[PDB]
Image (spheres, coloured by chain):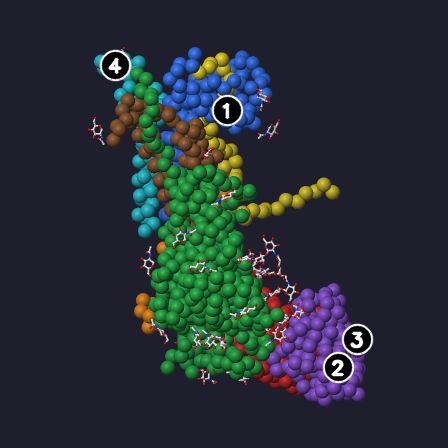
Chain colours: A blue, B purple, C green, D orange, E red, F brown, G cyan, H yellow
C-alpha cells in the first residue's frame, strides 16, 4: 500500500513508485479554504511534471540522464546506497545539493537540444 | 507619590515689572505642570495648562516653560490685579498633588 | 488581476504579501515597446481596490444612526477671531445610553459644514441621504508604499526613457515583477508625496489641445507645504449602545484661529515659472500664460483636499493660482475642516471622522499639479490654467504611467530544414 | 490550531441567524425569589420584571422572568441591568 | 459651563457631612469630578475623583476609608461624604472638573489638561 | 534572465527556451479574485500542453513536423 | 454574487482535476502523449 | 521542604484538543528524488 515501502531500501522501494504516484491526485469561508487546498495540489503536481519535461523525462517514473554524479554530493558505494539505505535517509543525506543537481539536469538537456539542431550526425 | 515644591515664597514686585516664579517636581511629570491663581474669597482659577498655553480668558501677560522637573511661570508686566497666591499642580499622575503656593505682593 | 505587496494600518493589513529586498529587473536590450498611460488598466485596478479597502475597513465600526436627531445649536462667539466667526456651532441633544429606557443630554462642538438648519433646530447634514459610519480610531489609513505585482504568466514592463510623457514608443525598457512602491496619497488639486521628474518639469496630457482633458504636471523639485490646526482640541466620548462608543470634540482650548497651510513664496513662484516654460512649448513663446483659481463647485472639488494627521482639510488655493506670465515670506492658504465626509464622489455611504486630540501639524511635499485650460479660442492668445478638479484615478495614473502589463505567449512556429524523423 | 479555529467558526456561524436580544437590555425591576428556598440557594435567583417589545412597534408588554444572579447586576425591589449591557449585544 | 455647590454647615467631631455639586452645560458623564480641599492657611490638597460614567473612584491616601463618593446621572449631580469628622477638617471644599480624558473599549485615557469650572466652595467647620 | 532574449534574433533566442517556461507556473472578494487568477494560469498552461500533445510534440521544447511551409 | 462565483470555481477546478486524472493514467500505463496506444496485456475471452 | 503543590488549571481550549491529537502528525509527500546509478541516457 501507500508509503508501505517507506522503511524499505532504495532498491526495494523503487519498485513501488506507481502506488505513490497515484495518491497525488485522488458557508463561504469553508468553501474558499477547500478551493485553496485543491488548487494548490494541482499546482504542485504540475510543477513536478514541468521539471521532468525540462530535464527531458516525460511519462516515466524512472529516467536516466547524462549528468555525472559528483563525489562531493555523496561519496558512497552503489551497494551501500541501494541496499543499505532508505529513501528518507538519502533525501536527508543530499538535501544540500538539491538545487545544484537540478540546475545541472537542465543544462544537460539544453545541450542535448543544441546537439539535435544538427542534421549532421555529430559522430 | 510625587512631591511638588515652589521656591519664591512672599515675592514682591512693582507695577510694570516682570515677575517670575519657579516650581520643582520630584521624579518628572512629562511636561504636565499646571498653574492656578488663587485670590482670597474666590475659587482658584486655571491659568496655564500643560506647562505652556493659556486657559481661555486668561490674559496674554501670562506665560510659562520648563524642563522635566524645573518649571517657570512668568507675568510679563505686573498689574494691580495680580495679587494672588499662585499654585502649581502635577496633572501627570493619579494622586494629583499641589505644591505650596507662593504669594505675590505689590512693592 | 494584480496583487499588492509591501515591506493596525489598513494598507499593511491588506498588502500582507512581503516584498523582496534588492528586487531585480531585466533590461531588454533592442526592445521597443509602445505605452499609453491613458489606457492603462493598472490605474483602474488600483482605483477599484482602494475603494474596496475603505469599505472593508469601515465595515465593523460603530454605526452612528442613533445620532440623526434634532439638535439645538448656537454659534460659538467666545474668543473667536473674525476669520473663524460663524464656523463653529455648539450643539446639544437627548442621546441614548446602553440601556434602552434611558437618555442623557449631550453637548458637543461641530463645524458648520457638517450641520444644516432644519427650518435654532439643526440636523446632521447626512440625515436626508444616508447612514453614516464612524471610522474606528484605532485603524490607520496612513498611506505606505504599495508595490503592485504580476501573477505568473504575466510580466510588467517598465519604461525608463527620461522624457517619456506616457504616450507612444519607449526604447529603454525592462521587465519587473513588482512596481516601485507607490504611496497612495489621496488629494485633489495638488499631488502630494509622489515621485519627481529627474530632468525637467514634464507635462503629460491625453489630448493637449482638448479643453475637456486635464493636464498632469510632474515637478522635478518638491515644494514644501506646512499645514496646521493651531488650537488644542479635547476629545470626549459617550456610550451609544452596548459595546459602542462615539467620539466628539468636547471643548477647544485657546482663542480660536483658523487652520491654514504655508508654502515658501519664492519657491512657489520659481516652480510656477518652470511650469510656464514647459507650457510655452505647446502653446507658443509669444502667448500669455495666466493662472487663475477654480471655477466653482462642491467644496471637495474647488479646494485642495487632504488628510493631515487624520484630520480632513479643505484649503483655498486661490492664493497660489493668481499670476500672469508674459515673455523670507510664505503664502498662507486659509483652510476649513469637516467631519462628515462623502468620500470617492459617491452619494451616501458617509463616514464620520473622529476628532483628534491636541494640536495638528504635518509637512508634505508638492510633487505635481492637476491643471485644466479654460476653454477658449484664439482670441488674444492668452490662455488660463486653473487648478483642475479631477478624478481620483488621475492621482494613480500619474505614478503608474511608466508601467504596462502584458501576457506571455510561449508557442510559436517558424520554418526550418528538419522534417519529422520517421 | 486548526481544530480550535474551526470550532470557533462553527459557534460564530451557528448563532449568526438567531434572535438578537438587544431589545432586552432595559432597566429591570427585581426582588429575591423566597418561595421554598433551601439555605444553599438563598439569593441565587431573582424575580425580575420589565417592559419588553412586541410584534408591533407601538406596543409594549410586561414580562416577568427568573434570572440567576450571575447574569444580573445591580445599577447602584431594586433596579438591575443584564451583565453584558456595558460590553456587547447578546444573541440568543 | 457651571458647577454649583451647597451644604455649608457646622458639624460636631465624630459625625459625617455630605456635600453636593450640581453640574450643567456639559455632558455629565463625560468628565471626571474632583474634590479639592482648602484648609485655612496651609495649601490646596486633592481628596479624590469620581468617574460619573461608571462610578470608579480614586482617593488620596489620607482619606481612604474616611471618604466616599457617589454620582447621580438622572439628576446631574455629584456628591462627597466625609464619614467621621475632626476639627482638622475645617476647610473650604471645592468641586472641580477635569477638562480632559475619555473612556473607550480599552479603558480610560487621561490626556492631562487641568482643572476648570471650579465651584464656589463650601465651608464646613468642625467644632462645638 | 526571463525575457532577456526578447530583443535577440530568433536563432539566438531559441537557445534559451527553458527560462521562459519555468516562469509560467510560479476579505472574501480578494480571496475569490486570487483563486480565479490561479485557475486561469492553470487552464492556459494546460491548453498549450494539449496542443503539443495533439500535434505529436509532447514533452519537447523544439519539435519537427511534416507540415510544409507555405510561401504565402 | 459570492455564491455564483464559488460554484463556478468549483466547476472549473473539477474539470481540471478530471483531465489530469486521465492523463496520469496514460502516464502510468506507458501511453503518455498518444491518442492510440498498444500495450502488452492480452485480451481475455472472459 | 520538597513538597510540591498542584492545582487545577486550563481554560485554554487548545490544551483539551492536544490530548486527542497528540499522536497525529501531518506531512507532505515529495515524489521527486535523484540517486546515482550506472545508467546513462542514449
Ligand atoms: C507626506 O510625507 C510625510 C513624511 O512621511 C508625512 O508626515 C508624517 O505623518 C505621520 C502621520 O500623521 C506622522 O506620524 C506620527 O508620529 C508621531 C510621533 O512624532 C514624533 O516622533 C517622530 C519619530 O519618527 C518624529 O519624526 C516627529 O518629528 C516627532 O518628534 C506619533 O506620535 C503619531 O502617533 C499617532 O498614531 C498612533 C497610532 O498607533 C496613536 O497611538 C498615537 O496616539 C497618535 O495618534 C504618528 O505615528 C509622522 O511623524 C510625519 N512625519 C514627519 C517628518 O513629520 C505626511 O503626512 C505625508 N503627507 C500626506 C498628505 O499624507
Ligand atoms: C496645547 O497644549 C500643549 C500641552 O498639552 C502645549 O504644549 C506645551 O507647549 C510648550 C511650548 O512649546 C512646551 O514647552 C511644552 O512642553 C508643551 N507641553 C508638553 C506636554 O510638552 C501647547 O503649547 C498648547 N498649544 C496651544 C496653542 O494651546
Ligand atoms: C521632500 O523633499 C526633500 C528634498 O527637498 C526630500 O529629502 C531628501 O531626500 C533625498 C532622497 O534621495 C536624500 O538624499 C536627501 O538627503 C534628503 N534631504 C534632506 C534635507 O533631508 C524628502 O524626502 C521629501 N519628502 C517626501 C515625503 O518625499
Ligand atoms: C504661516 O506664516 C505666518 C506668517 O505669515 C506664521 O504666523 C506668525 O508666526 C510667528 C511665530 O513664528 C508670530 O510671531 C507672528 O505674529 C505670526 N504672524 C501672524 C500674522 O499671525 C504661521 O505660524 C505660519 N504657519 C505655518 C503652518 O507655518
Ligand atoms: C516647515 O517646517 C520646517 C521645520 O519642521 C521648516 O524648516 C526649518 O526652517 C528653519 C528656518 O525658519 C531652519 O533654520 C531649520 O533648519 C529648518 N529645519 C529643517 C528640518 O529643515 C520649514 O521652513 C517650514 N516650511 C514652510 C514652507 O514653512
Ligand atoms: C414573580 O412576581 C409575580 C408578580 O407578583 C408573581 O406572580 C403573581 O403571583 C400571585 C400569587 O402569589 C398571583 O395571585 C398573581 O396573579 C401573579 N401575578 C402575575 C402578574 O402573574 C410570581 O409568582 C413571582 N415569581 C416567583 C418565583 O416568585
Ligand atoms: C453650549 O450650549 C450650552 C446650552 O445648551 C451652554 O450652557 C450654558 O452655559 C452658561 C455658562 O457659559 C450657564 O450659565 C448655563 O446655565 C448653561 N445652560 C445649560 C442648559 O447648561 C454652553 O456654555 C455653550 N458652549 C459654548 C462654547 O457656547
Ligand atoms: C526491515 O528490516 C528487515 C531486516 O531483516 C527486512 O527483512 C524487512 O523487509 C524490512 N522492512 C521493510 C518494510 O523493508
Ligand atoms: C563537483 O565537481 C567539480 C569537478 O568537476 C568540483 O570542482 C566541485 O567542487 C564538485 N562539487 C560541488 C558542490 O561543486
Ligand atoms: C549543508 O550541510 C550542513 C551540514 O554539513 C548543514 O548544517 C547546512 O544547513 C546544509 N545547508 C543546506 C542549504 O542544506
Ligand atoms: C450665526 O451665524 C449666522 C451666519 O449666517 C448668522 O446669520 C446668525 O445670526 C449667527 N447667530 C448668532 C447667535 O450670532
Ligand atoms: C430632552 O428631554 C426633556 C424632557 O425630559 C425636554 O424638556 C428637552 O427639551 C429635551 N432636550 C433636547 C435637546 O432634546
Ligand atoms: C439635504 O439637505 C441639503 C440642505 O438643504 C440640500 O442641499 C440637499 O439637496 C438635501 N439632500 C437630499 C437628498 O434631498
Ligand atoms: C538607455 O540607457 C543608456 C545607459 O545604460 C543611456 O546611455 C541611453 O541614452 C538610454 N536611452 C534612452 C532613450 O534614454
Ligand atoms: C508626447 O505626446 C505626443 C502627443 O501629444 C506623442 O506624439 C509623443 O510620442 C509623446 N512623447 C514624447 C517623448 O514626446
Ligand atoms: C529642474 O529643471 C530646471 C530646468 O530649467 C533646472 O534648472 C533645475 O536645476 C532642475 N531641478 C532639479 C532638482 O533637477
Ligand atoms: C486633440 O484635440 C483637438 C481639439 O482641439 C481634436 O480636434 C484632435 O482630434 C485631438 N487629437 C487626437 C489625436 O484625437
Ligand atoms: C519659440 O518658438 C519657435 C517657433 O516659432 C521655436 O523655433 C523656438 O525654439 C521657441 N523658443 C524660443 C526660446 O525662441
Ligand atoms: C476665485 O477668486 C474670486 C476673486 O478674484 C472669488 O470671488 C471666487 O469666489 C474664487 N473662486 C472660488 C472657487 O473660491
Ligand atoms: C479664497 O480666497 C478669496 C480671497 O479674495 C475669497 O474671496 C474666496 O471666497 C475664497 N474661496 C474659498 C473656497 O475659500
Ligand atoms: C491676485 O493678485 C492681486 C495683485 O496683483 C491682488 O490684489 C489679489 O488680491 C490677488 N488675489 C488673491 C485671491 O489673492
Ligand atoms: C518671481 O520672482 C521674480 C524675481 O526673481 C519676479 O521678477 C517675478 O515677477 C515673480 N513672479 C511673478 C508671477 O510675479
Ligand atoms: C436579597 O438578599 C440580600 C442578601 O444579601 C439582602 O440584602 C436583600 O435585602 C434581599 N432582597 C429582598 C427583596 O429580599
Ligand atoms: C413599564 O412602563 C411604565 C410606564 O409606561 C412604568 O410605570 C413601569 O414602572 C414599567 N415597569 C417595569 C417593570 O419596568
Ligand atoms: C460592566 O459591569 C461589571 C460589573 O461587575 C464590571 O466588572 C465591568 O468592568 C463593566 N464593564 C464595562 C466596560 O464597564
Ligand atoms: C542588439 O544588437 C547588437 C548588434 O551588434 C547585438 O550585438 C546584441 O546582442 C543585440 N541584443 C540582444 C539582446 O540580442
Ligand atoms: C497554401 O498552398 C496552396 C497550394 O498547395 C495554395 O493554394 C494556398 O493558397 C496557400 N496558402 C493558404 C493560406 O492556403
Ligand atoms: C483471464 O484469463 C484467465 C485464464 O488465462 C482466467 O482464469 C481469468 O478468470 C480471466 N479473467 C477474468 C476477469 O475472468
Does residue B20 show up? yes
Chain ID, mark 1: A
Q: Quick one: D15 or F28, which is closer to the camera?
A: F28
Does residue E35 show up? no
Residue to which mark 4 is pinned: G43
Residue C280 is tagged as: none
Chain ID, mark 2: B
Residue to which mark 1 is pinned: A104
Label whose residue precedes the other's in the sequence (3 or 2): 3
Residue to which mark 3 is pinned: B7
Label 2 packing within 10 angstroms: few (<14), some (14-19), many (20+)? some
Looking at the rendered image, the disc whose residue lies closer to the viewer, 1 or 3, is: 1
Q: Quick one: D61 or D48, which is closer to the camera?
A: D61
Residue to which mark 2 is pinned: B18
* Quarter occupied by residue B35: bottom right
Position of F3 relative to C324 (above/below): above
Ligand 5 location (quadrant):
bottom right
Label 3 packing within 10 angstroms: few (<14), some (14-19), many (20+)? few
Q: Are marks 3 and 2 on the same chain?
A: yes
Chain ID, mark 3: B
Disc 3: residue Cβ within 8 A of ligand 2's nearest atom: no
Q: Position of residue C31 (x, y in %)?
A: 43, 40
The local secondary structure at tag 2 comes to loop
Label 1 packing within 10 angstroms: few (<14), some (14-19), many (20+)? some
* Residue at (64% x, 77% y) in the render: B54
Amino acid at each position: 500500500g501507500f508509503l508501505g515501502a517507506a522503511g524499505s531500501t532504495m532498491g526495494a522501494a523503487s519498485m513501488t513508485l506507481t502506488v505513490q504516484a497515484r495518491n497525488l491526485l485522488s458557508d463561504t469561508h469553508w468553501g474558499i479554504k477547500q478551493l485553496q487546498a485543491r488548487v494548490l495540489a494541482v499546482e504542485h503536481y504540475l510543477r513536478d511534471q514541468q521539471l521532468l519535461g525540462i530535464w527531458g523525462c516525460s511519462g516515466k517514473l524512472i529516467c536516466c540522464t547524462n549528468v555525472p554524479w559528483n563525489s562531493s554530493w555523496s561519496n558512497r558505494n552503489l551497494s551501500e546506497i541501494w541496499d543499505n539505505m532508505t529513501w528518507l535517509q538519502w533525501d536527508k543525506e543530499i538535501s544540500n545539493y538539491t538545487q545544484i543537481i537540478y540546475g545541472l539536469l537542465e543544462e544537460s538537456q539544453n545541450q542535448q537540444e543544441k546537439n539535435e539542431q544538427d542534421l549532421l550526425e555529430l559522430d | 507619590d510625587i512631591q511638588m515644591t515652589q521656591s519664591p515664597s512672599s515675592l514682591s514686585a512693582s507695577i510694570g515689572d516682570r515677575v517670575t516664579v519657579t516650581c520643582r517636581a520630584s521624579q518628572g511629570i512629562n511636561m504636565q505642570l499646571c498653574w492656578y491663581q488663587l485670590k482670597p474669597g474666590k475659587a482658584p482659577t486655571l491659568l496655564i495648562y500643560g506647562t505652556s498655553g493659556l486657559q481661555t480668558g486668561v490674559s496674554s501677560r501670562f506665560s510659562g516653560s520648563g524642563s522635566g522637573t524645573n518649571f517657570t511661570l512668568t507675568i510679563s508686566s505686573l498689574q494691580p490685579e495680580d495679587v494672588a497666591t499662585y499654585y502649581c499642580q502635577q496633572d501627570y499622575t493619579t494622586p494629583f498633588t499641589f505644591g505650596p503656593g507662593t504669594k505675590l505682593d505689590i512693592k | 488581476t494584480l496583487f499588492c505587496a509591501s515591506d493596525h494600518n489598513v494598507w499593511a493589513t491588506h498588502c500582507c504579501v512581503p516584498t523582496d529586498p534588492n528586487p531585480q529587473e531585466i533590461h531588454l536590450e533592442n526592445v521597443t515597446e509602445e505605452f499609453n498611460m491613458w489606457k492603462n488598466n493598472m490605474v483602474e485596478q488600483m482605483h477599484t481596490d482602494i475603494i474596496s479597502l475603505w469599505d472593508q475597513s469601515l465595515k465593523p465600526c460603530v454605526k452612528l444612526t442613533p445620532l440623526c436627531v434634532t439638535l439645538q445649536c448656537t454659534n460659538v462667539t467666545n474668543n473667536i477671531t473674525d476669520d473663524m466667526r460663524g464656523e463653529l456651532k455648539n450643539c446639544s441633544f437627548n442621546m441614548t445610553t446602553e440601556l434602552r429606557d434611558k437618555k442623557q443630554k449631550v453637548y458637543s462642538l461641530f463645524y458648520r459644514l457638517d450641520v444644516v438648519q432644519i427650518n435654532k433646530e439643526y440636523r446632521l447634514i447626512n440625515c436626508n441621504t444616508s447612514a453614516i459610519t464612524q471610522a474606528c480610531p484605532k485603524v490607520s489609513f496612513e498611506p505606505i508604499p504599495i508595490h503592485y505585482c504580476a501573477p505568473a504568466g504575466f510580466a510588467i514592463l517598465k519604461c525608463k526613457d527620461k522624457k517619456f510623457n506616457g504616450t507612444g514608443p519607449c526604447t529603454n525598457v525592462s521587465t519587473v515583477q513588482c512596481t516601485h512602491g507607490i504611496k497612495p496619497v489621496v488629494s485633489t488639486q495638488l499631488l502630494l508625496n509622489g515621485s519627481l521628474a529627474e530632468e525637467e518639469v514634464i507635462i503629460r496630457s491625453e489630448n493637449i489641445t482638448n479643453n475637456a482633458k486635464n493636464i498632469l504636471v510632474q515637478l522635478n523639485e518638491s515644494v514644501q507645504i506646512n499645514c496646521t490646526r493651531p488650537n488644542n482640541n479635547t476629545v470626549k466620548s459617550i456610550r451609544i449602545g452596548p459595546g459602542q462608543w462615539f467620539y466628539y470634540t468636547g471643548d477647544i482650548i485657546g482663542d480660536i484661529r483658523q487652520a491654514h497651510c504655508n508654502v515658501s513664496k519664492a519657491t512657489w513662484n520659481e516652480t510656477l515659472g518652470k511650469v510656464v516654460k514647459q507650457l510655452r512649448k505647446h502653446f507658443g513663446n509669444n502667448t500669455i500664460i495666466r493662472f487663475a483659481n477654480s471655477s466653482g463647485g462642491d467644496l471637495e472639488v474647488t479646494t485642495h483636499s487632504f488628510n493631515c494627521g487624520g484630520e480632513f482639510f479643505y484649503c483655498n488655493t486661490s492664493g497660489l493660482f493668481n499670476s500672469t506670465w508674459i515673455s523670507n515670506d510664505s503664502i498662507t492658504l486659509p483652510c476649513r475642516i469637516k467631519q462628515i465626509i462623502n468620500m470617492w464622489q459617491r452619494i451616501g455611504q458617509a463616514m464620520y471622522a473622529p476628532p483628534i486630540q491636541g494640536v495638528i501639524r504635518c509637512v508634505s511635499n508638492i510633487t505635481g499639479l492637476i491643471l485644466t485650460r479654460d476653454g477658449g479660442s484664439t482670441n488674444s492668445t492668452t490662455e488660463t490654467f486653473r487648478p483642475g478638479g479631477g478624478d481620483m484615478r488621475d492621482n494613480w495614473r500619474s505614478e503608474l504611467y511608466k508601467y504596462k502589463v502584458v501576457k506571455i505567449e510561449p508557442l510559436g512556429v517558424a520554418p526550418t530544414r528538419c522534417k519529422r524523423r520517421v | 490550531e486548526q481544530m480550535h479555529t474551526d470550532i470557533i467558526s462553527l459557534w460564530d456561524q451557528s448563532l449568526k441567524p438567531c434572535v438578537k436580544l438587544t431589545p432586552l437590555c432595559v432597566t429591570l425591576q427585581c426582588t429575591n425569589v423566597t418561595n421554598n428556598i433551601t439555605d444553599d440557594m438563598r439569593g441565587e435567583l431573582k424575580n425580575c420584571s420589565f417592559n419588553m417589545t412586541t410584534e408591533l412597534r407601538d406596543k409594549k408588554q410586561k414580562v416577568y422572568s427568573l434570572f440567576y444572579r450571575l447574569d444580573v447586576v445591580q445599577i447602584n425591589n431594586k433596579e438591575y441591568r443584564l451583565i453584558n449591557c456595558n460590553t456587547s449585544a447578546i444573541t440568543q | 459651563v457651571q458647577l454649583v455647590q451647597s451644604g455649608a454647615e457646622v458639624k460636631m467631631p465624630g459625625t459625617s457631612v455630605k456635600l453636593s455639586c450640581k453640574t450643567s452645560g456639559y455632558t455629565f458623564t463625560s468628565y471626571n469630578i474632583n474634590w479639592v480641599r482648602q484648609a485655612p492657611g496651609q495649601a490646596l490638597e486633592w481628596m479624590g475623583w469620581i468617574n460619573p460614567n461608571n462610578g470608579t473612584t480614586d482617593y488620596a491616601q489620607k482619606f481612604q476609608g474616611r471618604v466616599t463618593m457617589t454620582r447621580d446621572t438622572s439628576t446631574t449631580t455629584a456628591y462627597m461624604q466625609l464619614n467621621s469628622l475632626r476639627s482638622e477638617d475645617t476647610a473650604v471644599y471645592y468641586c472641580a472638573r477635569a477638562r480632559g480624558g475619555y473612556e473607550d473599549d480599552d479603558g480610560y485615557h487621561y490626556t492631562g489638561y487641568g482643572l476648570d469650572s471650579w465651584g464656589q466652595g463650601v465651608v464646613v467647620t468642625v467644632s462645638s
